[PDB]
Length: 195
DNA sequence: CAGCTCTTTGAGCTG
Ligand SMILES: [Cl-]
Ligand SMILES: [Mg+2]
Ligand SMILES: [Mg+2]
Ligand SMILES: [Mg+2]
Image 1 (tube, rainbow, N blue to C red):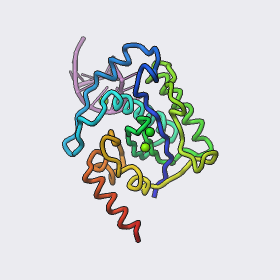
Image 2 (cartoon, rainbow, N blue to C red; image 1 turned 30 degrees about the horizontal axis):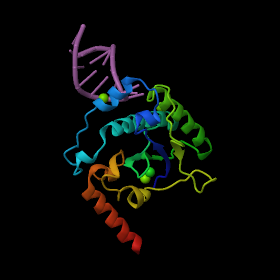
Image 3 (cartoon, rainbow, N blue to C red; image 1 turned 180 degrees about the vertical axis):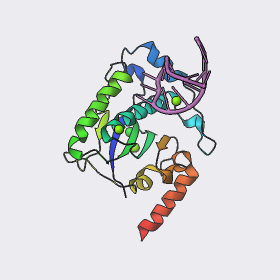
Image 4 (cartoon, rainbow, N blue to C red; image 1 turned 60 degrees about the vertical axis):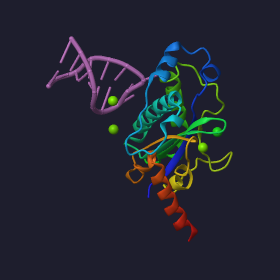
């Protein structure tokens, strides 16, 4: 099996509060992209907040683009955008291959700087700890998990908490945007787990 | 149709 690190990015969801003074161009971009559900999806599109998703997807792609240059390969990932009770956030589960825990902090710090530069027009998001690596315990090492984390924690999310998900892991391709498939994989996970 | 372009990163689109 492969192993994964997790980075949680709190995605700006109120431009006036999080990106004070940002140019109108940012607003035009985020409000102008139209999203459509693939036919395999069984999600209710009306529950998806498009401007926030547009930002999350841009963050995701910039993140993975930079990550791959660090890892030197097309790293495996499962990313899920969620609308939490306090924050909209991206759960970025990325394979550890080619990235040591010792250097992970620095690499993530560089990606954060790139996000600020190429996504937020040089404006630092006014959200505390908006880019955080999941640790073993508060004040510990970087947490490493296996794919079992996906059906245990990510898959069971439903709308409106679940906003969208992406993955290059074949086992979870249908699950990304299909509730019925997520339910099937979670049920299988619980069955095996109870034993 | 071979590149140029865009909150890209590669493939749709145009000179
Ligand atoms: Cl939250
Ligand atoms: Mg290379
Ligand atoms: Mg969450
Ligand atoms: Mg493209």
